[PDB]
Amino acid sequence: YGGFM
């Protein structure tokens, strides 16, 4: 996760 999608 992290905000790539």
Image (cartoon, rainbow, N blue to C red):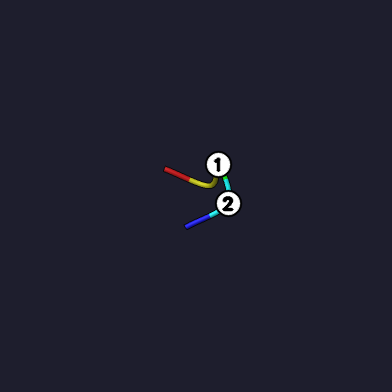
Query: In this rendering, would 1 be left or right of 2?
Result: left
Residue drawn 53% across the image and 47% down it: 4
Residue drawn at (58%, 51%), measured in percent from left and top?
A: 2
In the image: residue 3, left or right of residue 5: right
Question: In the visual, does 3 lie left or right of 1?
Answer: right
Question: Helix, strand, or loop for circle 2?
Answer: loop
* Outermost residue toward the front in this view: 1
**Towards the viewer: 2 or 5:** 2
Measured as percent of width and height from the top left, residue 3 is found at 55, 41
Q: Residue at x 41, y 43 (%)?
A: 5
Alpha-carbon distance for marks 1 and 2? 4 Å
Check if mark 1's residue and mark 2's residue have beta carbons within 8 Å: yes
Q: Residue 3 carries which label?
A: 1
Amino acid type of the residue that numbered disc 2 sits on in the rendered structure:
Gly
Q: Mark 1: which secondary structure?
A: loop
- Mark 1, Cα crowd under 10 Å, few <14 / some 14-19 / many 20+, is few
- For the image, the number of numbered tags is 2
Q: Which amino acid does label 1 sit on?
A: Gly
Which residue sits furthest left? 5
Give the residue pinned by disc 2. 2
Residue 1 in the image: x percent, y percent? Answer: 47, 58
Q: Is residue 1 above or below residue 5?
A: below
Horizontal placement of 1 versus 3: left or right?
A: left
Residue 5 lies, with reference to residue 2, above or below; the image says above
